[PDB]
Length: 265
Image (tube, rainbow, N blue to C red):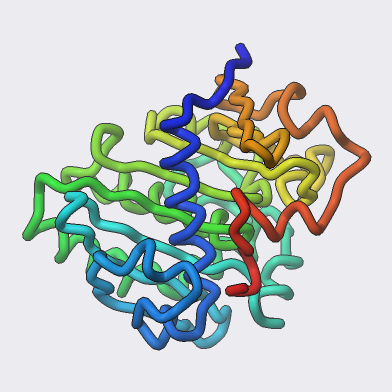
C-alpha cells in the first residue's frame, strides 16, 4: 500500500542521511576525524578504517557506535571523474554470487576493489561484538555500492542475515535487472530506499534498458515540515517518485532532509 513515515522512521532516516553526507568530507574519508559541519551528530562513533581505492576511487569506512550497539559501514557517492566514468559504465554484467542475475558493471567493479579489505574489518569487528547489528548506508553511487555490500555480507553466511543487517540508501541509482531486484527481496534484508522529491538519480539507468529497483521507497514529498510517503511494496512501484516523472530535478538530489549530500556543505 502506501502509508506515511512515522516521525520515528523519519528520524532514523536522517541519521543514515547524515552519515552518508559526512562521508563526502575529506576530513572523514580519509582524514578519518569527525571534523565536519554535521560531524558533531555522529562524533560518538569510533571510525575503524577508511579506504580510497585507486582505480575506481571507491571511498568507504567502518565505524562502531558502542552506545548504539552498531557497526556502521559507509560508502561515499561520486566525487571524482573515476566515479563518474564508473557511474556511466552500465553495461549489465553477470551477478557472480547469483545465477541468472545481472548488475550494472561500473557499480560491481567499484565494490569489487574495496570489497575484500572491507568485508574483513566488518567481520573482525563483529567477531568481537556478535550482538551488535550492522547498518550499511550510502548516497547516489554510495547507495549502489552500499547495496552490493549488504549482499556480499549476507552471502558470507557468517552470522549476518535479516535480523541483524540493515540497508539505507538515498537518491540511489538502480543496480541490476528484474532478477537481481528479485533476489534482493529474497534475502529479506531490511532496506529503506529514500528518495527526495523530484530527484533524478533514482530514475537512472532507465527501466527499459533492463533496470529495476528493490527496496521499500521512502519518498520525501515536502520539506517543511518534512513529510515522507512510504510505498510498502519491495520491488519498484509506480506510486512514489515514479509518478512525478518527467518533471525531475538535480537540485533535489543534493539535499536530503535539509542536509547537503554531495558537497560536504
